[PDB]
Length: 277
Ligand SMILES: C[C@@H]1COCCN1c1cc(-c2ccc3c(N)[nH]nc3c2)nc(N)n1
Image 1 (cartoon, protein in one colour):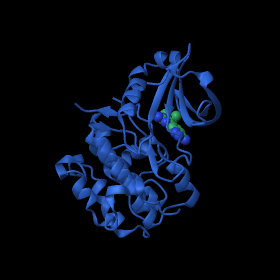
Image 2 (cartoon, helix red, strand yellow; image 1 turned 135 degrees about the horizontal axis):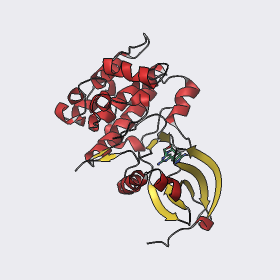
Image 3 (cartoon, rainbow, N blue to C red; image 1 turned 135 degrees about the vertical axis):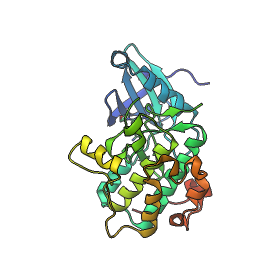
Image 4 (cartoon, rainbow, N blue to C red; image 1 turned 30 degrees about the horizontal axis):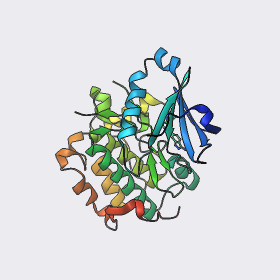
């Protein structure tokens, strides 16, 4: 194993992201010219806010992930005040940037990028890990325009908290729980947003959004691709045991076999060339 890295090992540059308890900065490792997204955390603030379990959860999950559709944790170190996590640099940034940029995706891009997310969730769920806060903001795009999912402090490992309002599953609002199905609900929202250009549950504030969620109060624009629409209806189901892809629905086989994915080769998505946006 290589030595423990230190801040002097890098030339830091721009801020790539900001969270409540962290900041992600682009850094070039001097010895290699390699670029990394270094997530920087202030020890005192983490302790002060009782966030140690989250940071720990992230380091632990992101270390064990070994799949192209995920941001990778490459190393950690600290100084007197700070924790540094060396992450994959996803040069093209957030999927959200692209939804905004181009408005809404065509069927080819929707199908392709949905398939990668699905293929990612299949990997994640196979390891007994639930993201819990999946969204266009943490589904990033690398230089080659393949997805790289990040942001795992709120993940749960199978053998309390609430994600972003638009993507919160109903089980979370009605009994504090989360299952793999919760990610499949997030997926349903994300497909809707790729197609429609907006998340399906929208309102003046969080309360109102939550209220629409528990009543399943949303609907499709006219232009929505019919197969996409049908797929979204199989995901946005109040009963979590009845979402396509969950264990009670017999998993990812039936999900991947949905007619929306007719033209997908599931086997080597990462090797395929993404459709142009
Ligand atoms: C600060 C944000 C929001 O707040 C919660 C914690 N978040 C993150 C953010 C990133 C992140 C962001 C941009 C990136 C890029 N361009 N390449 N890699 C990146 C990794 N990675 C993790 N793990 N968590």
